[PDB]
Length: 39
Image (spheres, rainbow, N blue to C red):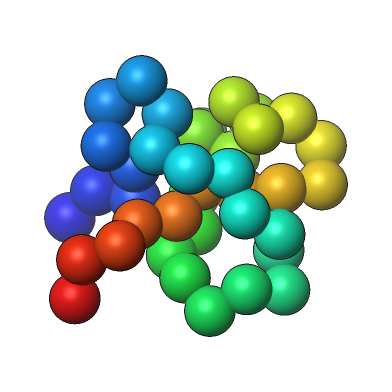
């Protein structure tokens, strides 16, 4: 469903094994994206 938690989740590198967004990757800025921890 959701690729973050609320305040922003956690910022990770683009070359990572976790979820990704376009609207919330801007919270991390330019060069990172938002990820999750659930399965």
